Image: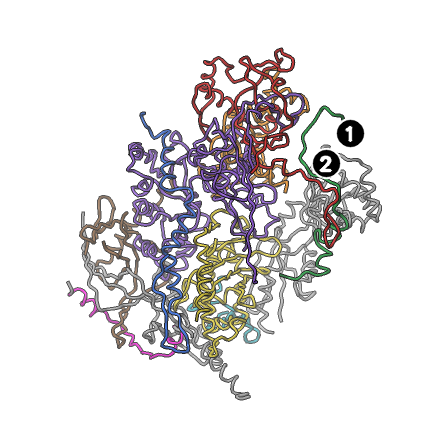
Amino acid sequence: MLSFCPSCNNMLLITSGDSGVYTLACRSCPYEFP
Amino acid sequence: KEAAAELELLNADHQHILRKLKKMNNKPERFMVFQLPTRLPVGSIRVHKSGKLSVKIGNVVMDIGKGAETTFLQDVIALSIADDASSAELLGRVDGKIVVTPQI
Amino acid sequence: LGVPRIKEIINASKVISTPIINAVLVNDNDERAARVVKGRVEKTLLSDVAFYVQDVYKDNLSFIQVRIDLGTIDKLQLELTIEDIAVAITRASKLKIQASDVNIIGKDRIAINVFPSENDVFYRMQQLRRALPDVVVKGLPDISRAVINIRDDGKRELLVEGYGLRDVMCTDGVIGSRTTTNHVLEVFSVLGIEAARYSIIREINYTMSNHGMSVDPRHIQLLGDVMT
Amino acid sequence: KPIRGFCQRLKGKQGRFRGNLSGKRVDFSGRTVISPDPNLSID
Amino acid sequence: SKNRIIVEADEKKGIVQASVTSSTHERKSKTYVITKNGKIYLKHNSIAEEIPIAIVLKACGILSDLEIMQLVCGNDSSYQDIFAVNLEESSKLDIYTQQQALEYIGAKVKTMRRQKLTILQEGIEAIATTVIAHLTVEALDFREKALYIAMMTRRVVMAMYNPKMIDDRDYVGNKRLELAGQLISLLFEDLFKKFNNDFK
Amino acid sequence: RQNRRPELGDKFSSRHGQKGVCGIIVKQEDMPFNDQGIVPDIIMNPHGFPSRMTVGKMIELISGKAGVLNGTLEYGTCFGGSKLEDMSKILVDQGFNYSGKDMLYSGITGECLQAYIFFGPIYYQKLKHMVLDKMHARARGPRAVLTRQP
Amino acid sequence: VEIAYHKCDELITLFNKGELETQPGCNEEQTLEAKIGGLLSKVREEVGDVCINELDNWNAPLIMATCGSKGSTLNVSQMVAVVGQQIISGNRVPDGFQDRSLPHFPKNSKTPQSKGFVRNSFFSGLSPPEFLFHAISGREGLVDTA
Amino acid sequence: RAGVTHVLSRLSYISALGMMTRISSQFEKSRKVSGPRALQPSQFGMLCTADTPEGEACGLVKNLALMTHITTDDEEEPIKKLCYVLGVEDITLIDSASLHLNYGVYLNGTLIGSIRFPTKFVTQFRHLRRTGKVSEFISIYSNSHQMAVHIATDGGRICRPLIIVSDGQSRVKDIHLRKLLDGELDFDDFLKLGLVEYLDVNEENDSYIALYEKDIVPSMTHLEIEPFTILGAVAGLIPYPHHNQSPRNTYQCAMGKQAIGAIAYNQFKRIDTLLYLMTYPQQPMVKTKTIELIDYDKLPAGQNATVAVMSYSGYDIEDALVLNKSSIDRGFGRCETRRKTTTVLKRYAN
Amino acid sequence: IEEFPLKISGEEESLHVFQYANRPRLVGRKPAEHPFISAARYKPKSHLWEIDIPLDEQAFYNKDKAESEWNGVNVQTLKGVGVENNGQYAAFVKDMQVYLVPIERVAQLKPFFKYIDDANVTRKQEDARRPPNPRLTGSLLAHKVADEEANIELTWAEGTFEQFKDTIVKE
Amino acid sequence: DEINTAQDKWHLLPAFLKVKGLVKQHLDSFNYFVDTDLKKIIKANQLILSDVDPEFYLKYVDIRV
Ligand SMILES: [Zn+2]
C-alpha cells in the first residue's frame, strides 16, 4: 500500500494513539504521522 | 528486426556519455566508475566517424565497447582509507557508470 | 460420457464431475426476459458491481468505503435494491463483524466501520479489505455458472452448473414439472425414490447411445431395480 | 522384508480367495497355437 | 535434472515448487515452497515446521523490506497485491532486524541431536543457512543465497497469477542422462572407504 | 544340438510389422506359375494393405524386382532412396509389366486367372516362438504341497 | 488444399485487427482455433469423396470398401489422396516449446502445415517435419489400450 | 534401485546391439498421468522415435538416435571469469530496480551478472566458442517469457551436432567436403575450424534449423546434416519407412530383436544357454544406408523369397501364410536349436 | 577524430565505495544531498562499516515513545560488508585528461537496527535476573571473529583536495 | 564424379561413425573413470590414522590399474 517509512523503508502501522487518534507510526523506527 | 533495436541504443549512449564527459571537464570533484578488462594477453578515449567511441589500451589490443548500462536508484560516495587511522575523508558522489569491453 | 461416466453412477458418488442441471423456461422469446432469470439464478458477485474501494480517514475513523455502478444494474438487467447489499454484509459468518453497524451514505456509496490481543485496528480492516469483495449479494449460493443456449426449436433453455436443485424449483420463471438434472442420488433426496430409479434408467442409455452400440433397454431396468 | 502372515495372504491379488478359491487350476488341459481351416464344419 | 529448480501446478492442495540438490558429501536434500491458503511458506526435511519467507531473507541480511517487495514483484503490476498478504507475517512476530531473524529458525529445528557439546544457539543458524539450497555456498555475506530464494519465490507468485507459466517435468531439458562409468564410481568410493575403516 | 523344418505354426514376419503364422503346406503342383514357370514361395492375401496401410511393401516389391533383372542391389532409405518412375523404366525394358502387376496361370485347373496378380521377391525373416517348444499338456501330474493344485 | 490455406490466411491475420466472432461457448481466443479444424475436416472428407466417383471399377481398395469386408472410404483416401490432420485427445498437435512445435518452424506461426496438418499422401511420401506429427498419434494408438 | 544390469540378448546380431542403446527410466509412480507415457516433440534427432515397446513397458523405455553425443562437465569457474571480460556486471552491486528491467545471465540456474542487451553478449560468445577458446559443450538457451538468459555447463545432457549457417549462404564449402574424402580432414577438424557445433535440446529453442539446401532463407541458421538420422540402429532396417504407417514401425522394432539369423564369426565356438541359428541366410534385396554402417549385411537375418500376394484355398484369411512343400524340401529356412546344459563336480567336507 | 588519453595513477591507496539503499539519486528531478555522517567505525579482518546518522527532531521524531523501551536516541546506524571485485576503477575527469585509481572494495550499507537489538540483549538479561538460579569451521567460524575485535573511531572529515593534487603529480 | 554439397553431405556421416563409433557412451565414460577418477578417490581417503600409536600413518600416493 506504498507504506514505506523513509530512512528504513520498512513498513507503516496504524497505531491507536492518544484519545484513540488513528495516527500511523511503525515499530523499530522512531517515526510518526497522522 | 528486434536484434537491430539496440545498435541505435549503442548510438543513443555514445552521444549521451560524451555530453556527460563535456559538462564535467571543470573537474568539480566529480567521479565516474567503470570496469576494465583484466587478463591482458594507458590508451586513449577517442571518437570515430559519426558517433563511435573506442579505446586502444594495449599495444595491439583494441576495445570498441562502451555502453552506459544501469538504472541507479541509490546513492554512492567514494572515501579513501589509509592504514586504519584518522583517515576518513569523503571524496565525492559518482554520477555515471559505464563499462569497457573488447570485441570478439 | 465414457467409462468415467459409468463409474460414478454405480458408485453413487457424492462429488460428481460437471453437475449441470436442466431448466425449461416459461417464455419462448427473449423480450429481455429469457436472461432475467439467469441474473436471478447466478451467484452474483459484488466485485463485478463494485467499482472503487478505499479506506477514508478524517482523523478518528476506520471504515472501508464501497461505491457501486448503477449503470451495471441497467446493463445486465438484474433486479435488486440498495438495502439488500447492506443486509448481505452481516449475512456472511466467515467475516467476524457485529450484526448492526452498517450506515448507508447516499445512493451509490456504502461504508462500514469497525473498532475494538492488541493492534487489531490495523489488522481487521486490512483482513476485511480483501475479504469483503468476495461475497454473494443475490442469487443461488451453491451454483457456479449458468449458461443459456438455444435448442433446435425457437424455445430456449438454461443450463446451470451447480449442486443445488430444490431452490432451482423454488425460483420464478421456471416450472416445477419439467426440470431434469444429473447426479441421481440428490434426486433421491428431492423427488422421492421412484424418480431416482427412472433417472438411472435415463442416464445410462443416453451415455451409451452416443458411442454407437446399443445393448437393450431391458438390461438397465434390472440394474435400476437391483440397486433400489 | 516385512514378514508374511495369515491376513497378509488372505487378501491381495491372487493370494487367496481369487487364485485358490475363485479361480483354481485344472487338470487335463493344453495350450498351443492355432491355425485356420475352412474345410471342416462349424461345431 | 538435479541441482535445478522445477515448478509444479496442483489443483486442490495448493501449488508447490521443488528444488533438489546433492553435492558429493552426505547431501540428499530437496526444498519446497508451499502456498498455504494464500501465504507462502518454506518447509525442509530438517526443519520441523514451515516458515514464511519474509524471515529467512532477513536472516541473510536483506532486511529493508522495500527491497523485498521490489525483488519479488518489481513495479506496476498485480504481483504487489498478490504479495500483500505475505509481508504481515513478519509484522506479527515483530522481528524487523537481522539479529532476531536467525534464531527464529533455530528454535524450531530438531536436527543434529547436539553433536557438539558446546552450542552457541546463535551459531547453529549460520550452519542451518549452510545446509540449505546447496547449489551455492557462502562465506560471510549471505548475498547470493538470499536472492536465490527470491528468484525461486518470483516463480511461485507468477504461478498463482496464471497457471500457464508452470512447466512440466517431462520436458527433455529437465532430464539428466546418467551413464554407467559415472555410476559405478558412486559405488566405488562408497565401498573403498568401507575397505580401510575396517582395515584400521 | 537339433535342427527342424518350418512346419505350420511357426511365426513369420515381414520386416514392415506383419506378424504371420504358417497356415498349411501345399505341394508344388497346386501352386500357380508364371509364363516362365516360376513358382512363388510364400502366399499372403491382399486383405492387409488397406487396413495396415503398409505402402512400403507395395513399393519395395517393385524396387526389388527391377534390381534383380538389372543385377544391382537397390538402396531403400528413409526420406529418400530410389524413386518409382526411374524404377519402372528398368523392368519394362526387360519386358514385364510396368508396375510389376503380372499375370499367371492356375496350377490346379490350368487356365488364366480373371484378375491380374502382383508378384516379386520380398524379404521374409523368421522369428522366435516356434511351436515345437510351446505345445504341452498335463493330464494328471504333480500337485502343489500347500494347495494340492496343478 | 490451397483453397483451405488462403481461407486460413485471412483467418489468421486477424490478430493485429482484433476480430472475434464470439460463438456461443465463451471463445476467448479460440475462434481462429476451433474453426480451422472445421474447415480442415472439410478438405479431409471432400477429397476422399472425389476418388470414389473418379476411380475405375475392378479396383481392390475400392471393391473391398464397397463391401463391409475390411476398410472404409476414409482408409483408401489416406492412401491415395491425403491423410488429414492428426488429433491428440481433442487437440490439433499443441506447441512443443516457445509457442511453436519444432526448430524447423518460425516463431509463434499459427498455421496448419506447421502445427498439425500434413497434406501429402502415403503414396507421395512424407517430409522429415511431417513424419514426426504422424508419429505422435501413432503413439496414442498404443497408449490408450493400457 | 534394482535391475540396473541386464543379460544382453543374443537372438540376432542387432538384438545384441539394440540393447546397448536403450534407456531404463525411474518409474516415479506417475501411473495415472499420460504425460511421461506419451511422446514429446522435443525429440527429433535427440533420440529415436519409432522403437518403443508395448504392453506393460509401453512408454518408459526409449532408445538413442543415430547421431548422438553425451556431454560432460568441464568447469564452471573460468567461464565466470570469462563473462566479466565480456562486460557483465557483478551480483553484489546491482539495485533491485535494474535486475527486473535488464536481463540476467543464469549460471546453472543461478544469476551472477545482470547483463543488458544480450544479443551482443550471446553472439560474440558463439564466435568465442566456434573459434574454440571455450569448450564446445555449452548452450546459450535464452527465453523471453521471463527476463533472463541461461548458461549451461553441467554435462551429462543430450546433444547432437549440426553445421553452422551464418546467412543466406551456408558454410558448406564443398572443397572441404572433397578434402574429407582425400583422408586428412576428419570430423573433429570440422568443429576445430568452425564448420560444425553441438546443440543440446535447450539450444534448439534459439535455433531455426533448415531442412534442405533448397530451403535456405536469409533468415535461416544451422542447416541440418542428414534428415534420415532420426531412426535408431534397431529401427533403421525398415526399407522406405516414410511411405509406411508409423504404428506399423513399432510393431517391427519390437520384432526385429526377435529375428533369427547369424550371430558372430565364433558362433561355432561359444557355449551359450539357448541359441538358435539359420542354416542358409541371405542379405536383403532392398538395403538401407543405415544397415551398411552397422554391417548388418555382413551377417544378415532372414532370407528373401518370391511372394505372390493373393487369396488361395481359403487357408489365409487374415494375415496367414501359404507356402509349398518343395521349397522347404529345397531348404527354405531350416533353423537349428543349440542348447547348453551344465553341472559341477562338487567336493564335500569329508 | 579527437583522442583523450587516459593514464593510471593509483597504488598503495585502497578506497571503498558505499551504497545507500534508502537514499535515492534524485527527488523530483532534483538531485538530493548525502546525509551528514555523525561518526564512523571500521573493524579489520571482518570489514564492517557502522556509519551513525542523525534523524531530525520533534517534527517526525516521536521522542517520548522512542526513549522508553530502547533508550537510544538520535542515532541510526547501518551495516555494510566491504565486498571486492576485479575491474571497477574510479576516475575523475580533467579538462581533456582523465586519471584512474583502482577501487579496492565496495560496500552495500543496509540499515542495522542496533537499538532494538540492544534493548533485546538486556531483555535476555532481565528475564534471567528473577530466577537467577535453579569442530566448527567455515562460515560460522567467520561470525565468532567478527563480533569480538578492536573498534576504531574514524574521524569523519571532508578532504581529498590533497588527494586531488597527489594524482596529478604522478606521471 | 563431379562432387557437390547438394546430395553428398551424407558422406561425412560415415566419417563420424568411423573415428567416433556407436558405443561412444560406454567406452568414453568408463575410460574416463580408469584414468582420472581413480586418482580422485584415494586423494579423498588418503592418510589412514589411528588414535593409539599416534606417530603411525599410511598414505595412498597413487593408483594404477
Ligand atoms: Zn519504518
Estimate the spatial distance between the alpha carbons at disc 2 and disc 1, rounded to whole Å: 65 Å
Instruction: Using residue B68 as the reference point, say whether residue E187 is left or right of it.
Output: right
Foreground tag (2 vs 1): 1
| Residue named by callout 1 | D43
Which residue is at the front of the view, H52 or C140? H52
Q: In this view, does I39 lie above or below H195?
A: below
Q: Which chain is red?
A: F
Instruction: Using residue C154 as the reference point, say whether residue H206 is left or right of it.
Output: left
Which residue is at the front of the view, H306 or G55? H306
Disc 2 residue type? Asn
Magenta part of the chain: I142-169
User: Where does the image place residue D24, in percent across and percent down from the top left?
Assistant: 75, 47
Which hue belongs to chain B?
brown
Q: The yellow chain is which one?
A: E
Q: The blue chain is which one?
A: J
The quarter of the picture where residue H255 lies is top right
Which hue belongs to chain A?
cyan
Residue extending farthest front: H350
Q: Is residue J65 above or below residue F118?
A: below
Q: Which chain is orange?
A: G
Q: Is residue E148 above or below residue H192?
A: below
